[PDB]
Amino acid sequence: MIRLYPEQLRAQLNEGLRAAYLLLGNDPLLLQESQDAVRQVAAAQGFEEHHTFSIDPNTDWNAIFSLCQAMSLFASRQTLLLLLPENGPNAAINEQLLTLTGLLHDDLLLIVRGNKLSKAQENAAWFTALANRSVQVTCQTPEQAQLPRWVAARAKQLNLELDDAANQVLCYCYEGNLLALAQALERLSLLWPDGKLTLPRVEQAVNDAAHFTPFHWVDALLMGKSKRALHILQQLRLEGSEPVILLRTLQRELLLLVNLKRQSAHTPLRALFDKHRVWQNRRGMMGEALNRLSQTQLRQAVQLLTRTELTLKQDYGQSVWAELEGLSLLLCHKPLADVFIDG
Amino acid sequence: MKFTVEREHLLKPLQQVSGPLGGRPTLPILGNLLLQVADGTLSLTGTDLEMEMVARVALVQPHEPGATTVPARKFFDICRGLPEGAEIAVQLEGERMLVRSGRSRFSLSTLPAADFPNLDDWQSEVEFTLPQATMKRLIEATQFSMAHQDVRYYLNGMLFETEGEELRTVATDGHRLAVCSMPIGQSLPSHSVIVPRKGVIELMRMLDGGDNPLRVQIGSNNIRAHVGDFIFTSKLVDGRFPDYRRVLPKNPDKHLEAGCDLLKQAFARAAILSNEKFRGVRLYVSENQLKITANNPEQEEAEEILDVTYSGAEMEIGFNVSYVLDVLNALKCENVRMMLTDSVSSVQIEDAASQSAAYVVMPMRL
Amino acid sequence: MKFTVEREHLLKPLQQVSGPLGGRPTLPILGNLLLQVADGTLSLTGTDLEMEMVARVALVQPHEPGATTVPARKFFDICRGLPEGAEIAVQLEGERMLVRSGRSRFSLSTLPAADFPNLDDWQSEVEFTLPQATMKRLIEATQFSMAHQDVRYYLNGMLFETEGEELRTVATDGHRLAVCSMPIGQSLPSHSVIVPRKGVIELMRMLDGGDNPLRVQIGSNNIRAHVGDFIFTSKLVDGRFPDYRRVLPKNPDKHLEAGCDLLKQAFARAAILSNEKFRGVRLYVSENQLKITANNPEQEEAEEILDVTYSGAEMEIGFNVSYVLDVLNALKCENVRMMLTDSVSSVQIEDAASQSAAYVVMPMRL
Amino acid sequence: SYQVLARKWRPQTFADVVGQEHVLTALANGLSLGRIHHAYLFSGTRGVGKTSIARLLAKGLNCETGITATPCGVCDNCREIEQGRFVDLIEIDAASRTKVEDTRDLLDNVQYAPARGRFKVYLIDEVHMLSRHSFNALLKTLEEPPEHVKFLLATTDPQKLPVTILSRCLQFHLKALDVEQIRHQLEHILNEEHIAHEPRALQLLARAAEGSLRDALSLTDQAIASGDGQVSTQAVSAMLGTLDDDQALSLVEAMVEANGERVMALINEAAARGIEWEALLVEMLGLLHRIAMVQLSPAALGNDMAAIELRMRELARTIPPTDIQLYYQTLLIGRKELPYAPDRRMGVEMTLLRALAFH
Amino acid sequence: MRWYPWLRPDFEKLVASYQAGRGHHALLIQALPGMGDDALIYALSRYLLCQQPQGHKSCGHCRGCQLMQAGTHPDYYTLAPEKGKNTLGVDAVREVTEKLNEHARLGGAKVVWVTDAALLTDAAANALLKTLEEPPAETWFFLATREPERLLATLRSRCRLHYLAPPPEQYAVTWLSREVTMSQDALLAALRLSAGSPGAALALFQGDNWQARETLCQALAYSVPSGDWYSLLAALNHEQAPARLHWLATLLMDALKRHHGAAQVTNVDVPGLVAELANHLSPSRLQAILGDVCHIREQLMSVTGINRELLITDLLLRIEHYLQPGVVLPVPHL
């Protein structure tokens, strides 16, 4: 099935009545955007009878009219938003999905927003007979990389200048968060009279409806900035953050650091920062930390990380907040080395 | 507050007024009947705020003006449960209402009324006195499509259209519509008003008989009735929802008159082990015959053959059979004339004495 | 298979027997009744895995080896929907038991008679017959004192034991028992015949004056009851039926000859502003009169003054009026003398007029 | 199906139940006097006599000889008590029930006063199960219930049972039952039973009954079931997986020998028969304890490792106190940690390994 | 599982016993339900419900048997766990139980057998105490566990235990071997690794578990010298991690055995590897390590939200930490 990118949704929308315009993707900004465009043009297209009706994981189904000549008290085509289960339509669903494919879907102009389906669903007969009439709109988000581009086009959504200096700083700090970034650009535009972004201006007031990712801290740590990383966490507190997340993300990078530290101490930095991942900008911070972080001193650190993780997670000890202070310096070993009793 | 009534006198109001207040609807006080000895009267009032039913009872029998309010049930049942005629000496005696039977005393809980809201009397834009029967003629043979509830707005009350001398009702749910109109000859500035369903009911409850010529005053706001001591006011959604004009068979051509009931029976038999999914019975209807393929997904079919005075092309037209008995029967009509379309459109079930009375259902195939 | 039946003939059998049908967590073919028109009778089994109502139809209508079990109702529905008298012929063919009676025909499904799980019915010893007349009282009077969720015995059950030539039964809730006594019967052995809750109902049904008199082979095993065109047979739950002589008040003896009715009325009234939970009316029967003082905790109070020829000082006992009325009413007897032991203790109530229906409930609180 | 003895061994009088005199007496005593609480709390192990003291009491309240220290055998009420049906008495397993719901209903019926009983007596057992709400709901009537109504609480544990509840019961804590108290009672019992008892087995069971007379009794039924008649040692030693062998010390030694293999290969086969590890463990531990004790006093022990006393001695003295403590310690922790191992067999190996690593 | 031959003699006694009402109606079969207990159980019900007819038969004939075969025997129950759960809830229980207070409902005794009583719930169990203890008429109850350990004590107070170990290893291997090809060492290594239970032994050779066993085995032999354990993350990182965690343990343990001089291993599916462990690692740390393998195996199962991986990794590094000097080397305790 045709994959469409939301920005190109008009291609299939417009050209013809796509049955199931399946905005599977996940950037909510993208999903939202792919939804309303079908609808808008759908509602305009005599499907004003527009209802939303999820499809539970539950068998669900209700309005399965898809032609029956029942109406003439209120004739028209209607349109039916399906919000999908987690992974998509399951059995019953799939079934009654495969039924619709079978019929004019008359009055049931399919708009299936959701996420990526599961494979078997996509091989499941319903998701087989939609094809060629439906539209899959990949509503998936930019890499760090494509993110500025997008961001930059997106500026002009707001038409304001934005500043690409700022874009980046948005692309990093809102690396991957289109929606909030979109709203980000909104709050501040309002806030001023001018509402013209540019980097200086976006410093003075920063959208308190858009996050300052773990990265700031952890990256600060990459560097070895064992104080910097710490400060970002003072903030990550006042901010209320769930510790899980921090751990999660930290875990993500550090395990990446281990493995890359195994292979890196003999492989040029940062290439691997993107041969894997490690943002562009981090790549430097990251090529460093492999050199800084010698895999051994690195071992005890993991043992404390794990420790805290468990403290949380099995134990629900909420002192993981203090355990980290150790670790910062246990791991970094300071920007230098300075590895000490675990905690 | 104090009155004495007879159980029975009281009894009409004992229902009318009490009935939709039992539920203690809305506010408690609302769910209480207002007892009002005010004067020689004893009005009962059970407001809900959704309709309202007042019953009046004239009372010369001992009473002291005052008022009270008691739950709709507490009181009603005692009075009812009383033997008949019973001189139900009711007394607000402070805060217990001493309900005195004759050797069985009861003490209800009573607040003196001092609140208990009451609805818009408004000069009703169109007012008229129904000959009643029309009211049921219509009422009955048009409330089969009225939804109860209906996100299609206000189908949950009826579409009281006033148009000229005719009063038309429409109910629809979207697949089936009924119009019955009749004439009143009361030159009713047209409008359409959706009167609460609950209303319709109470109305129908106070449709009353004895050709109680039901005085109506539709406003748009309020609508008020007068059937005996039972004055019922509703607020109104005004509005309208579609009428049959459009629903209308694209083939009027096909006809099908047949006896409502032979037919009904046929339907009734037809609807057996018929479609569980949509009550889809695809009638292949000869010019004389009517043959209903009613399958059901349990691989059981029912087949009924029976004459019709059928005309126009015999074609399989599906229907929600369910619909069709509803009206057949509600429709006071012998032969029901169908005027079928082929099944794209509805078929015109009409009353014979459709005083404009179109009863239309769309096809529903199995 | 091509067995004809007499529609009508079958018409009542169909109902008697479908009433005891399924009602188990597993109830597939329990929903289908089997028929074989032996040619003579037919089977018209409605099993429950607990009781059965086999009807037959006397009919001579042909049959060919068509052992089938078709949905009880579908089949039924058809028979009635078809003219009666109508010689309801069927083709059993490919588990598709069609029915044709005129221009109506249907294709039902069939579940084979082969997996039909049935029940005990065996020639059950003893033979002893009670007229449905009293048998009725007997059943009425006792059947309501069922109580259910038994992990301990049969409350909802009921035992059958001829104590003497009498028969005495009992069902109880543990909070009221009902023992009616049917002088008639035989001395002929009683057997663990503890019929359920359900059965007793259909039986009760199989009496009314109507049917034949009710005749029983009281077997421990099963019993074999004879009423209507049925044959109603339980496997019986076999286990004791709790005591029933002790439960009689301690010296039920003050005779509270009242009229069961009046009382039943008064009682009905009193409960209202009686305790609203348990319906535990408290009584202070004024001698020769009566008096009752009820209060619903929740304010209110009800009071009556009635008469009971009651000597011996105020009975001052309250019991669950909820139980009581039930027996008044299952008490067809209208002079009911109560034999109480005046004091918050059990009161036996019996018909004053016979002793059949003797009934005991217990006081409420202490 | 087929009958048990445990129940059938339940009291009629205080004797049938071994121990808890504090309670027996506490009971005999309560009963006789007006020291009848409508709140009792029998807290003892499952049919240690949490349920037994209840039975005696019951018969005694609904002794139709009033309230009586002993329940005056027969009384109708008394003898039916331990038989089905008995209106006064209504008994309850709050086990199956957990719901509060179950708890609500219960409170309602106390009203209906028997048409012939003399204390509507209520017996709840296994109350722990019930939910919190179920618990708290009881406080109301533990305080002032309607008359006749009682609240014989028997609990295994009054622990899943609030302070306020205990606060509001006579808690006759039934303490536990000595192996011997048990052995004896059993010894007495089994012998009454036709089938030749079996001392070995009696003991095998006595210790094995786990301080609860009920099980004790249970065991037995069961031993017969699978010994298809007759209590015999072997069927019970085996039935019990019990090693009447000195393998405990054998291995201890082979650990000490630094002997790896012998220690280990032996366990593995034991595991094919799945042989009980614990039994084996407790023993080793004990020896060690004693030996050290034998060091302390090769007499001031109240040791029962006499058959090997000399062995004990021998050990005790030759091995410094210290090390004895230490052996004892190692394996104690390993036992602790034995189960943790995903073959059971595995956990014990570890224990010993660590010992064997200690030497 | 299936009925195996080694379920029969158990049955007979029990039915015998049952028939003699010496055999208590209760029953507990230690043996894995994986080593056959279920069929054994049900074989019993087969008879038991049909009232126990014939001396001892599984019952092929019988209305009880066949209606129980149809299952429509009401007497009959299978009384599995509850499916809104997956454990055998109280409610499930409450029902079948109370249906037995209505006697037999189509004759023959009832048999109400728990599939794997190992699987019961507590409200269920608590519920069942009184019913397993107290005998309702014609009830022969039949319970199944992996091991007896699958049940609570108070229950077992009343369980008429009919032990049932695993059948012997040899047979358990021959039995195991029939059905999985790969050397008896893998059968056994696995079987042994199964605490010798077949039923348990069998599962190993399925999947890529025993191939992954091997897999794992390989990476590790690299890991061990190299002090890169980290290589092993995956070999063991699995839905059967604990199992793979298990594969591994039995070798570590084999290396400590070599550390107590002991030829004996439980994974006779390679002794080289075993040697090297002991070899590159002091037992202290072998021993320390062995602890933890399970411990993770536990944790992978216990810690809510636990990164399977995270945990599989930490461990490798840390091992790797130990191989390393100075890095203090535990021994397990306190």
Image (spheres, coloured by chain):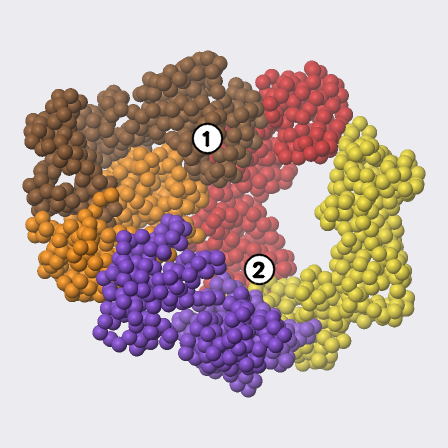
Chain colours: A purple, B yellow, C red, D brown, E orange
Q: CA distance from mark 1 to mark 2?
A: 74 Å
In the displayed structure, does residue C255 sit left or right of residue B70? left
In the displayed structure, does residue A31 sit left or right of residue D325? right
The front one of B37 and D164 is D164
Image coordinates of residue B275 in percent, x first then y, are 57, 66
Image coordinates of residue D72 in percent, x first then y, are 42, 14
Amino acid under disc 2: Ile
Q: In the image, what residue occupies the spot 57% across and 81% down?
A: A159
The front one of A101 and C145 is A101
Residue C88: mark:
2
Q: In the image, what residue occupies the spot 81% across and 39% down?
A: B112
Image coordinates of residue E181 in percent, x first then y, are 17, 63
Q: In the image, what residue occupies the spot 71% across and 28% down?
A: C294
Residue D214 sits above or below residue E318 on the image:
above
In the displayed structure, does residue C308 sit left or right of residue E192? right
Nearer to us of marks 1 and 2 is 1
Amino acid under disc 1: Val
For the residue labelled by badge 1, is the local secondary structure a helix, a strand or a loop? helix
